[PDB]
Image (cartoon, coloured by chain):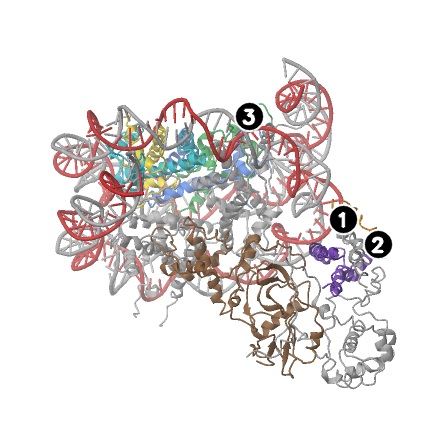
Chain colours: B green, D cyan, F orange, H blue, I brown, J purple, K yellow, N red
Amino acid sequence: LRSQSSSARAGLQFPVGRIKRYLKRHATGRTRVGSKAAIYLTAVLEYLTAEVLELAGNAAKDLKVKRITPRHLQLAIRGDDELDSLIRATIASGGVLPHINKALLLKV
Amino acid sequence: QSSSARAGLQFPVGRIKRYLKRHATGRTRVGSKAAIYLTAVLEYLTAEVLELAGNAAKDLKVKRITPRHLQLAIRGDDELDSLIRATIASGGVLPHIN
Amino acid sequence: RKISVKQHLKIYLPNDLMTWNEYDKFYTGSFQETTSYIKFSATVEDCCGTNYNMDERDETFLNEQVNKGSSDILTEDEFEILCSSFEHAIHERQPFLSMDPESILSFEELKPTLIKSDMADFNLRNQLNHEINSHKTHFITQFDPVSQMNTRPLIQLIEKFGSKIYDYWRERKIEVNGYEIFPQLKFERPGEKEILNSQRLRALHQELKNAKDLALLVAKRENVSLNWIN
Amino acid sequence: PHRYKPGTVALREIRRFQKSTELLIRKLPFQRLVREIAQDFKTDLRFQSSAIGALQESVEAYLVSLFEDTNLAAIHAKRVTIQKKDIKLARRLRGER
Amino acid sequence: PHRYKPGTVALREIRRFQKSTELLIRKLPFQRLVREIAQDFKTDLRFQSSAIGALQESVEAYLVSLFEDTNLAAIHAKRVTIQKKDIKLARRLRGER
Amino acid sequence: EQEDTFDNLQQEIYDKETEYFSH
Amino acid sequence: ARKETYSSYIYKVLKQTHPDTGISQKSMSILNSFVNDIFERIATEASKLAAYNKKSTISAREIQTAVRLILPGELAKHAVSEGTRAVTKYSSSTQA
Amino acid sequence: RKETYSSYIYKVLKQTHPDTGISQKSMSILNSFVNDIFERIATEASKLAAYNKKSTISAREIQTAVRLILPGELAKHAVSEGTRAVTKYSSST
Amino acid sequence: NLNRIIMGKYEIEPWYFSPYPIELTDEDFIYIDDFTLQYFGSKKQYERYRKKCTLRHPPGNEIYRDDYVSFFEIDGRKQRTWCRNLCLLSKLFLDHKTLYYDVDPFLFYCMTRRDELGHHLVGYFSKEKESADGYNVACILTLPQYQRMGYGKLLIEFSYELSKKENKVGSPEKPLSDLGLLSYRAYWSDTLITLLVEHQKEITIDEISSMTSMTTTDILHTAKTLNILRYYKGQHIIFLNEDILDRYNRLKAKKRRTIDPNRLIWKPPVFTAS
Amino acid sequence: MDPSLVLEQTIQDVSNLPSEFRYLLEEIGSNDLKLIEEKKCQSLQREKCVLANTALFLIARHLNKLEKNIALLEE
Amino acid sequence: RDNIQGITKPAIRRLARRGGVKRISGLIYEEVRAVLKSFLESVIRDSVTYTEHAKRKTVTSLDVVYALKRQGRTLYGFG
Amino acid sequence: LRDNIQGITKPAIRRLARRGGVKRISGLIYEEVRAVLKSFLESVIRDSVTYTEHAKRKTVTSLDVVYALKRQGRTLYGFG
DNA sequence: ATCAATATCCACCTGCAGATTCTACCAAAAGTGTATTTGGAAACTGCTCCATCAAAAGGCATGTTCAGCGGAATTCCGCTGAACATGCCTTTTGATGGAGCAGTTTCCAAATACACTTTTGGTAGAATCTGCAGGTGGATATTGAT
DNA sequence: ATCAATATCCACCTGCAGATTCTACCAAAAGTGTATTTGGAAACTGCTCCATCAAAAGGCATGTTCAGCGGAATTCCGCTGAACATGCCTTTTGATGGAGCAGTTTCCAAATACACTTTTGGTAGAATCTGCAGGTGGATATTGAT
């Protein structure tokens, strides 16, 4: 709509110069190709935007219109997509997968 | 004269500095730190080697071979966790039987 | 947006919120089923034998016109078979027949060819008859059609009547350039419309031959069961 | 003077507590352990709350995974009581000599 | 004929392959099986035959990995043989993903 | 008048059963 | 008192996914650390791969293979896709 | 077309017992051992290189790194020797 | 259409326009028999084949018959000539295959019925004699003799129970038949509710590759057919659903003619020469 | 051609006569249980040699190509 | 001093019934607190070295959690 | 282009478990230890081929599988 | 306790690759000076935030019985560790053999560093309101006495 | 098995952090318009590698076996936990209290890039000895049945 773009070229959603001086502050090599240094918008987006669609139903199931943390690494190791990298995430009281042995219940 | 002999021990310096140049993002650093940074291999590379040779007293395998090398530095146990990560061309394992 | 995976569970109960006119005389007769399955190993081409039959167009000169004063009785069952033969009794020896129906080769030089020719190795059962001694009865299977208990050998159709078989077999190749009444396919192309011998296999002449000697008496326990009625 | 079959309210405790993520511990004796065992190496050292809490629950996760682990090790040997050296070899097999 | 006892001649064969360290597998069925399960998700990917040397010692590495800890699981379980939930416990003990 | 090849042939199969396909 | 605030972008996109939806803040810092940790580790890997390729510019494509490899394959495909649709609108140094 | 390091390891070996000999699975395998312990010290350098919170790097990061990565007695006498050698480098004016 | 097909009982106007007059471009009235089902145009060779009757059961190998029908498995390599020619019936009609090479090894399963007039050739679906990409079923056709009973849908009840002793997967191929969908999912429809009525335990969707032999790229594809994938309750829940309370009453109160896994004899072959 | 391609033709049917072994011999010994009591009746004879004939004809239609494979692989 | 019994069978009653075991060997105490303390004094000791060479004898969580991110079980969430 | 499986390869166990000090086995875990070997290694060789196609190579190297083995995280001797 | 056939230990003896320590050749990171750096060395200030008590109540030890559950061995069996005549792709064994290297060579896209630059996210931090973690009762799920 | 005592589900509701979201400044950059540099790309191109190609040795491998011992299933002594009522201890949530840690200053020790100049640590190399794996031969462990 405008000639002045904020890199409006991406419909963009993430801060850009911040990732560029991120790129300047770990910067082991000297060069990361700059038009392809705009791919890092895909570097952020994804599973965080996957969990926000993942975390819908329980929040209304426990009748809660905003978000609280603790139901999340439970579904992470339950989420078969991310669970391979989801080992090093440990949370301040964000939980476990709780599970009871069926063999614990002797039905007596 | 040499950065071995100016540093006065066996090893030279600045190439490993260039490796930490090719490791770098602060992009420059002091020349005088590097020799003790260079020490880290030395004061490592002792910690495994002739520790074999207590077994050399009674067997005369006077060339070092690889499965001879891993015989009792493997028993030099204080680093040994870090070398379960060490893999190797046909290393070998030993008993602990119950 | 993703799709499901293994290992999971299912919640079951809880609180969730004009008929063509001519087949009746064409097929009657019954098939015998066994109580078990069938092993079948005979080709469908020799179930047909020849894939050749001849329609009304030439046999309106002969079936109701020549049978009037024929000395040997002339049917149709003897004739349609013999003129189906010799196309394959000569197929080894003119694969350059292709280009011209003027190059049909006449019977006067088919005399040493087709008289002692052998139709896809035709005559294999008569030298198979002498050790089998089906000499009284006549060599019939049901893989064979029943048109051989009635029909007669190849000689005394030729050497009584042979000068009039090739004759109208000749003129009706040039109108199609030598093709058959059924041109075979579009088979000029598959196109569109319009050291091992020396170790173990030498029992191949031992483990199928160990019953060929039995095979001369696989008949004999039924070849003994025949001469009793009459 | 009436009680049900012995063992039932533990199941309730499983439900609520593995369901829970509220902590357990007084901060003080835990960090008193860390201070007694760290002041030896240099006196006058302090610490921050997220460490004690997360360290607590992380080693809880450590142990409680070990508890279920040797649970199915005991019923793997078809029993319930785990041993010491069961959890030792599991954790040895997790990476610590 | 004379026949050795079950186990103590297994003890010398324990000592025999402990006395071994050497090469395990043949070249061929391994290299082709991994080659064809790579052939699918890209048509024919070359392996350095030297790196097939690296692959043969690589599959040495996986076999020594899994068999050292299956040894240790068997000596956990009070059992002479090894089986499934040994390796299940070891794998989730081991972190497959 | 007709039972001659009928009785002098039937020892072959028990001469055949242990002959070839028993080994 | 000298920081950056990262819950807003996911906050805006969370309401645009789920219409009136708020946040808890701890997970914000959890996953910001999580994403830049796994990002910097694949960065160090990618730079070393760009060292032992002996050619001196890090690309989109090799780190993209990294987020095809250790990122999981469905959302890896999603990653390639959304990066490519980003770049196929990253061509407009033009009028339309 | 490469450098070697094991020659330095040989002269260290004659500083130790010069007596022993060389197999070449063992010479190549000590070469790979020393190469990946070299990259190992490079790696723990990377992590300090991150969270120094610094931009131009000190030498106490070197001393503390060789203090911090490694077990008790070998690393202690290591850092003693390393300071000793660089201080005698410094005395070698 | 051209040169319309008088085949057995009920005729058809042929579907793809003229691969009956490939070179056959002058006649009108075409007479088809059943056994080898020869595509005879012309008149007075065909009743001559009624003199030529030697076959009361066709060349089809048998691993099955029920009370009613029998099943055919067709090695087209022993009988060479005709065992290509049956798709030319399809090439007039179901054009979705190739005649590009006179292809040697390719496989079938055709189909028949025991009629007291004789064995009744009643159609086929396609097959491959290999192991490449699913290689069981590609093209569904219920022949223009007769369509409208249940065997009009029972072409695809055959690949899967072969896969039991075969112990690997069979998977349909890309030239689909459009009406075959109302067999395709319709066959796989009640299969999902089979181990649903029991087995409330954990299922893996390749344990139904040990139950139904289905591949991962397609066992999920048939899953979302009944959009059966509710979540955010604790797992991916199949959601036992009130509409489907019918046909696991109606599969057992309006039971339908399916087969038995025991009465069949087959063993896996060996692929040898090329 | 070679000795190697001669086995390729001579296994499959060679593995199918055992199917013919496992299919044919049974009904020879089945249609004959009732008849010795007689010792249909006068017109059933025409089939009993026919199914014997396929127990006779079934073997030489192969040898017309088969036995001459020995001669070309020996010369 | 000897406050090892801060963690005990009430503690591991909760955090061991959470394991789903029922009957502990009711002398697991010393060794579980041992491995607990091995992790903790190890991880805090090199955290302390970092931060008191950064000249600070309190410790944040980030350094200590990177040191246990060497064993990989990293807490996040407080910066 | 042999698109056939031979992966049920071998009870090599008979010294897979005499390298260690463990007694008799009787197995049948063969199939899945094959599978777990193959699955782990295919996960690491798609790594190596992605490396090699970053280098746009046809093959993976001994060096490349060294990159694989360090990056799953057990460091490899003998091969640089 | 004892007989007696297999398996291994140590000085001696022979092929077999080869190690190593340097000659031929190199080459390029290295040793020290000089300018200009600049972050940090190191100290100063600000103002803390990890440390000190006081009132009650809320969980742990110790119970007494019990007890559900094994702790260590019974009989069986099965299935198999140690045997085995006799096949197997494999292994040497060079050779074919051809084709993506890698190492040099060679344009340009452009990333990156340069200085400007219109606005937009870090924080100060309150309005306000507002769902929101939970107190208090109805319907009902679980579960023991005999 | 049919009550009655607990326990989950659930309804409706009670004083909050406190989210949060917002103005408001406000630093404060990240997008705007050039510069200078290359590393990318890639391309050319002998070649050495890898995948076959074939064949007498060929140590395992194949099915096949034979009669042993944990595994399974299964046993009573004996009880360490386990069920919670009575006794007791350190607590949590509220009040002050101080030397050390965030953030900020002046001087300095060291370092980039450069400019000189070179040894030396590096590569392919093949002589000599030789080290080592490997083959020979007598004396010493090691078990299964009687």
**Helix, strand or loop for disc 2:** loop
Location of residue F2 by image quarter:
bottom right
Q: Quadrant of the N terminus of chain C?
A: bottom left
Q: Mark 3 points at which residue?
A: B55
Residue in front for this viewpoint, I224 or N21: I224
Residue in front for this viewpoint, I193 or K49: I193
Residue C85 drawn at (x, y percent): 78, 74
- Rendered residue at 61%/81% (across/down): I3
Mark 1, mark 3: which one is toward the viewer? 1
Q: Mark 2 points at which residue?
A: F5
* Circle 1/circle 2 CB separation < 8 Å: no
Mark 2, mark 3: which one is toward the viewer? 2
Residue B13 drawn at (x, y percent): 45, 39
Residue C176 drawn at (x, y percent): 72, 83
Q: Which amino acid does label 1 sit on?
A: Gln
Is residue I14 depicted above or below N62 in this figure? below
Q: Which amino acid does label 2 sit on?
A: Thr
Is residue N131 depicted above or below C29 in this figure? above
Residue C223 drawn at (x, y percent): 80, 59
Protein chain holding label 1: C
* Circle 1/circle 3 CB separation < 8 Å: no
- Say left or right for C71 vs C101: right
Mark 1, mark 2: which one is toward the viewer? 2
